[PDB]
Amino acid sequence: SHMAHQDALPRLPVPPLQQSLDYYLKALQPIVSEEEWAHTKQLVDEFQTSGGVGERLQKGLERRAKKMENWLSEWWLKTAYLQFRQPVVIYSSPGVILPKQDFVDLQGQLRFAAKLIEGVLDFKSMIDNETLPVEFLGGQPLCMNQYYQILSSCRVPGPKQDSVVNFLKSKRPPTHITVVHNYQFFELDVYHSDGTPLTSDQIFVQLEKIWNSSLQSNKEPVGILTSNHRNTWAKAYNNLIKDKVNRESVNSIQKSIFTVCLDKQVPRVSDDVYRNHVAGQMLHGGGSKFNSGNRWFDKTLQFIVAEDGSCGMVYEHAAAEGPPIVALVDHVMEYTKKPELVRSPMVPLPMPKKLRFNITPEIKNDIEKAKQNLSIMIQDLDIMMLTFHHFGKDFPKSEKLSPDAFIQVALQLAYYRIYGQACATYESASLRMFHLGRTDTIRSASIDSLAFVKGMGDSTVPEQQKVELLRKAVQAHRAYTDRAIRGEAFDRHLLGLKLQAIEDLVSMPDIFMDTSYAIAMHFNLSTAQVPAKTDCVGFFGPVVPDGYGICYNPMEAHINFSVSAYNSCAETNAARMAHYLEKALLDMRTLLQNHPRAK
Ligand SMILES: CC(C)(COP(=O)(O)OP(=O)(O)OC[C@H]1O[C@@H](n2cnc3c(N)ncnc32)[C@H](O)[C@@H]1OP(=O)(O)O)[C@@H](O)C(=O)NCCC(=O)NCCS
Ligand SMILES: CCCCCC(=O)O[C@H](CC(=O)O)C[N+](C)(C)C
Image 1 (cartoon, rainbow, N blue to C red):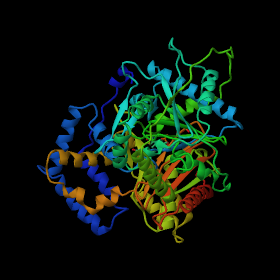
Image 2 (image 1 turned 45 degrees about the horizontal axis):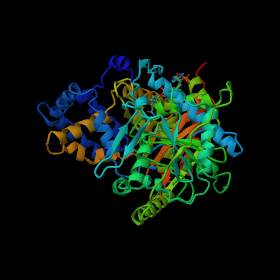
Image 3 (image 1 turned 180 degrees about the horizontal axis):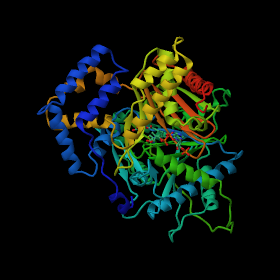
Image 4 (image 1 turned 120 degrees about the horizontal axis):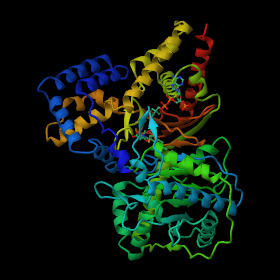
């Protein structure tokens, strides 16, 4: 970002070896057997002995930190995304459900879309001018690098690994966005010759031309190709761009500031599954027969505007994290609520260029294969959207407890109630207080949380006694959270030690081939909090076949929840997990209310 600000930021540290290993052993106690823990304990001692393997790997990481801006940056981006070969849809690209808008006709839909585009361009002005306000977390300045990765960027299919292109700072920065309607892409300039951005009224006029130039959905949904396996898409992509026209259209899409998807009307569904269907529409598009072909999942930022008033977005994870994305959302949404002023008669405008695609028998086959693949993915995705209206951050705070920790502890309780045991739990932690920092792992399953979930369901433990255990678990989780954001967690560290071993060309350390580590890294619960002023909520698929994907936005009086699971695993059920979570939160409130502290 603004290089001045970035330079004053501390560099991602490398936690002490013995410290991280100690935290690791503690986080394992609640998720592994005594026999397994005892063995790991032995591997740890040997691993960190003087003159041992761990010490050499640690030294390597410290050297890496001295010759790079962030010793973790490239490794993370690579292992977490660029090398992740599964489809980006559902398994990687997070989806976001925004507050439903009130437009009831085409003009209204296009009206909001125009306002949204203008709001994004407004936010972009701060990025180009580097005037974007500095943010804080834990009272520390935060990295703003992510904001210069979301716009005018795109992921690119690679035979072995993927790459990312960013034109935000190219010789002549893109001044156009891409609009998709009925699977057809259009190149739309949102800036005038002089350099000033088009007005909402002006953008609206352009969207109309675009909409009328693609009234029928007869064209092939070429964009659905971006939802297939990366290896398959890499090859299909290479073929697709062999045509001059096709390559030209793709280039326009990749360079576009961002994409706006004008989704078509979808079959009315039951009211008890409506929100789940809107979440699916934002995450994957619903299917090849709906709006899945009306997208380009390699594009970093995709804003979706439904015909029935619904709206949201889906973004490619290799670019940024949640906070930056939601920050842009809060600004855009708040912008669409701003009144109108200058309604002067706008001057004529050019016809948005239509990014055509020359289909061939081979390309057609690729599209069909993509449809088939996407159909399987969607059929296996189990989503449950839960709006916890009972309460929000308000109650936990009135109890002098961290809301997020309260929620995480509630999730642990809910899981234990269902399966009778704890499980490796992952909660995203922001490392933005460090230059180029992304995230680390907060492990919600601990000695204190397990002690709580056990005593909580113990009909032989005094209700007041469960209160102490509850507060202790919450405090323990808050402590872990504070350490994580300060670069004191151990997950990314341990990952670094393993990649370092690989780089040092030494045999894989036993500690990394240990069963305990496999268990610890197999997150049956993958979660993250998406704080936002806008009453929205994010969602993503589970990270493992037998796990859940839980995302939430804690508001003051309520909490927006999203729970995902796979139908391939009979042991998991999104609705059930959501219900136990809701009940878990309530029971914890009841417990605390039944035993006030003040007198
Ligand atoms: C882990 C994380 C979410 C915790 O955030 P947090 O703001 O500390 O969450 P908390 O629940 O502790 O605090 C929320 C509110 O409760 C309050 N609070 C916390 N502890 C409290 C206490 N003991 N008593 C009273 N109030 C308390 C906070 O002041 C805050 O108040 P606000 O509503 O006025 O802002 C954050 O540190 C982080 O890392 N976020 C990034 C996650 C991410 O990257 N997500 C996207 C992944 S792609
Ligand atoms: C709208 C975005 C909601 C959060 C998505 C998220 O948490 O992505 C995580 C990023 C990280 O922790 O590195 C990964 N995860 C989805 C697997 C938790």
